[PDB]
Length: 8
Image (tube, rainbow, N blue to C red):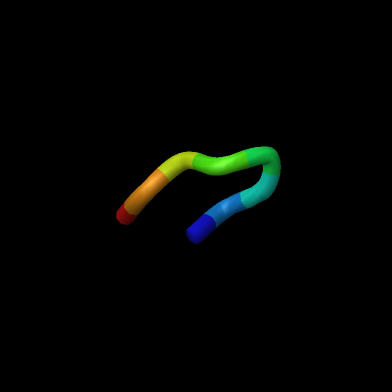
């Protein structure tokens, strides 16, 4: 989870 909320 990369802020503000991108999924990898």
